[PDB]
Image (tube, rainbow, N blue to C red; front, side):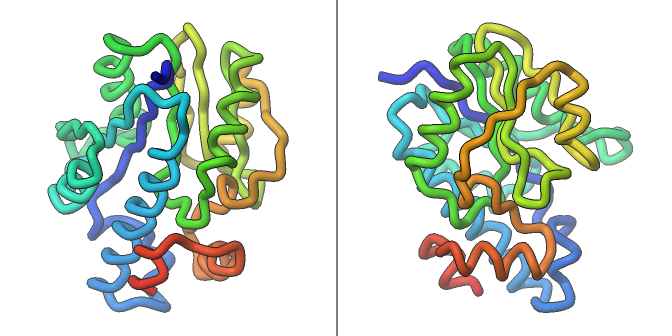
Length: 205
């Protein structure tokens, strides 16, 4: 059995992926965000090195979906006026997950084209470092952050790749297109769909 505690943080679905609003009705946009989480979780759950998957979210629909796939779920109590709610949530989940795992991996929940093998390989590569990350497709963001026997020090948000790099996290290379293809914009979604999205995202779009 595995040694990696995987964390995914998910914001309120109404707030999520607002740059997809031009191509989706609000209910369809929320459905796409949830479906991308489902496909990401499904791909991740195939990775043999995982001990657990923990989803932290204030969104009860996302909570139900994750729990319904056999993930651990943490309610996110982070106030609305917290200046950095994403990293606050990750750090909160980390404190819990750290009780049961020494090696923790934070994964974006909007990777609908993720293949199990891609994540497995990324984690194998990460084992050679204390802290490491995979940049997303366009290079400014972070698809995955990995910490082996040390604190994550997450710097997700704008310009996270650069911030992670500055923090001393080593950048992993490895094509892993499905791992890198996070979906923020319609262009990102087009790219993901060309790689091949999982069935939940296929249905939602």
